[PDB]
Length: 258
Length: 258
Ligand SMILES: N[C@@H](Cn1cc(Br)c(=O)[nH]c1=O)C(=O)O
Ligand SMILES: N[C@@H](Cn1cc(Br)c(=O)[nH]c1=O)C(=O)O
Ligand SMILES: [Zn+2]
Ligand SMILES: [Zn+2]
Ligand SMILES: [Zn+2]
Image (cartoon, chains in turn orange, red):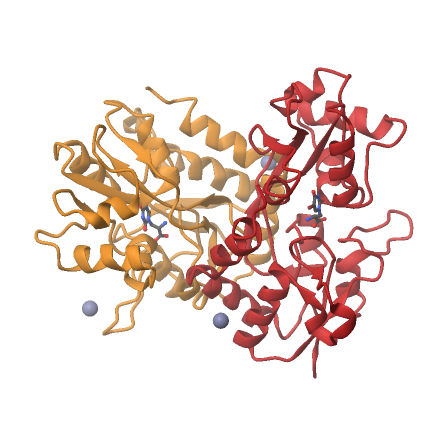
């Protein structure tokens, strides 16, 4: 049985090739996770079909209905067999799906235009002339919602009631907002993404300060999946072979344009 | 029943308290992993007994005898129920025991006596005046033994054949060797340990270059253990609540001597 892989369009993890018009199936896509999927499938010995998550979300549980959305939801309800994407390993998700050991390490970071008078999270929390937000239905927004750290909690009380909404549906929207806000908007996002964007023209953004936390991305499978064990050992093998480092250089700096 | 925890004397994870002869049981020890063990036990709801691994090793399988030694061996043969220490999550180990998601991220790094003209692994491999080695019998040594990467294999070729041995029995032994070498010995060790030593008197060592790889430490349990699931969720909860960052600051920098 062909394995249904759920993923999300997030550069440089999964992007449609420039010549996708003449391509079909998994060939239409390219990116870090596309290469990863091929490796995993090869080592675990299975055939697969890459599918972009229906609602374009990573995964969160509806407080009122208790229904899971995003890629997590597709695994939970059996719409997909495995998720290969920049999906953060978290406690709430681990309670409903399985995660392989991390294939990438990262942390929340700050993205600023360039010339923006901000160097840390504390700086952002000390002023109000510059707005800031995060992505939606993701671990970043949840981080601030659950954080007890003085600075992070203060930032949340602002973002929560901010008008207009400082949250964005997609990373692209957030980066675009930073670039066109004359430096009046800072974006909080996962470090790996921040670093990628800093190497993309117009080369007008930059990562400032250290990461606010430590976390990792993992390959997810529904609980009780016959793929779980094999996939986990596959990720470890690939990391130990140095393939994962090989893949990040390829998509992050070998293609950098700054 | 009381849970038997195997761990290892490796500063600052587990250390003998100054007046340990005056104390009993778990109170004889102090450190990052001692603090972590208490927290894992509280959150998982079990009583425990800290024990220091008999052979003072982390864990490897002897080719020929097929017997596992170190903390891994204590779990494999049922001498301990859980291992809470700076134990690296590796494929070969994952095949015989279970690991929680990582509680600490790190990579192999280079430690030099201040002033040593070395800035990378490539630098080390391209010269011979400066000797270098690793902790014997651990995942760092195995990384070089198993690596297929040119630079790292070249380093392995030299280290395995060096006489006298460039390998050391304990981290302290390696650090002392760097300190007494007048710059003629560099030490390859896990990054977080390198960082710890850099903050200890006489403040004569430092970490140089980037990490050679990326991996993490995990809490280990025997396969099929009834504790596995709970321990994993506890680690994720503790990381998300910021405790792990708190513990590193406490044992690394709050007590920094440089
Ligand atoms: N990895 C997250 C999604 N995600 C992604 C990016 Br990029 C970001 O900046 N913030 C997030 O929460 C998850 O798994 O929810
Ligand atoms: N973490 C390793 C042990 N270990 C420890 C230190 Br500190 C080091 O520098 N190298 C190692 O291999 C393992 O699990 O074998
Ligand atoms: Zn391969
Ligand atoms: Zn709702
Ligand atoms: Zn606690």
